[PDB]
Length: 219
Length: 210
Image 1: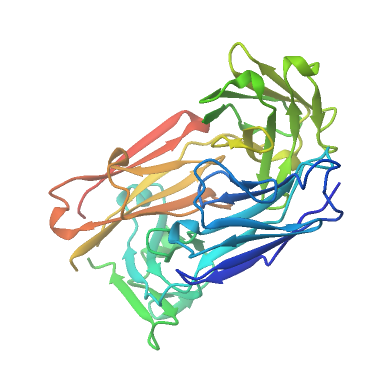
Image 2: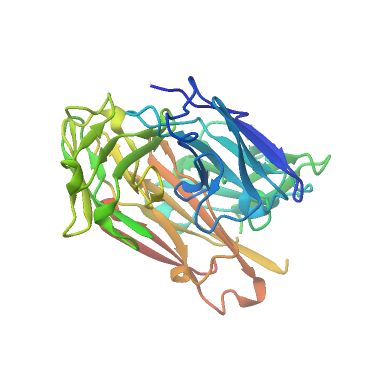
């Protein structure tokens, strides 16, 4: 089994600039005939992989001219001239020479380095449906921010709580190159009705002060 | 071209499951068909392979699925099959029906090898308790993955964020938010549609004011 190694694991790049991604194999995959059965793929978030380049340099159907593939033998380079926002995602490389099996690389995540964006924070008390079932989740949305680095703190009546918190990030959105995050503080109905103030705080590079949204059970 | 997978879902360890894949946009009979899977621990892993009538219906398998998985094609129905026998927890992942190596990819179906039961989701409305207003839906206590979220049957998509599901003792939990101009809610209704094909269930939750 030939091992495909992609470097680096992640790569930031601004729009308009170029980007290069390395993919190396255990052995030379040069067939007796022609060059390499070396294929490049782009998997946009939420989608399946899509063949970009085949046989080192041939661009597949509907691939823009800015995607180019270089390299020979064991080393192979995928290049992107003037990166666009729709180019973000995980780029893979496969090989079809020494088969079986057909092996892929670990994948390199292309991240668009966009300008700083502060999160738009929204807090939501539990719904009446969930309370009927004995649960009580408070939801905090932190939408359209950059960079991805962010901290969320849940405070209950001025006291910080860490257990019962569920966090979930989206991948970078190609429409604006931002990230979003969902933070959910899940409590039993019993504990929820023994407190009044619920607060999620966002600490992000864009502000020296945390972004705070709160509410009291006295709606 | 287009490749559409079918089947999958929740399977208890040791059970069996059949994957089917209908193809269009090309001639199904002149291409090598492969099944590829993806998971956080494996990455992209080639699983199987089948060739043409002019290739003895040749087949290849990965070293880990050999003897348990059977790839099969049907040029009449333009369908590939993957009878998966003696499934173990390691086989859990997203299975992509592909043509060539690997020219064309389908959307991919999700297979979860676990011995818990299928549970339909609970959908909770998230209403606010600015020129834009953000609404949400909370989807808790379902199994297995995936569920798909849309807003107003897909009519709203520009201001939607759908977050990946996290597994906990409460089964799966995910959330979705939509942002619309505040002058249009609640005059113009906003509804989240949660589809859970593993449980044959769909829930539509109209977000109303508190």
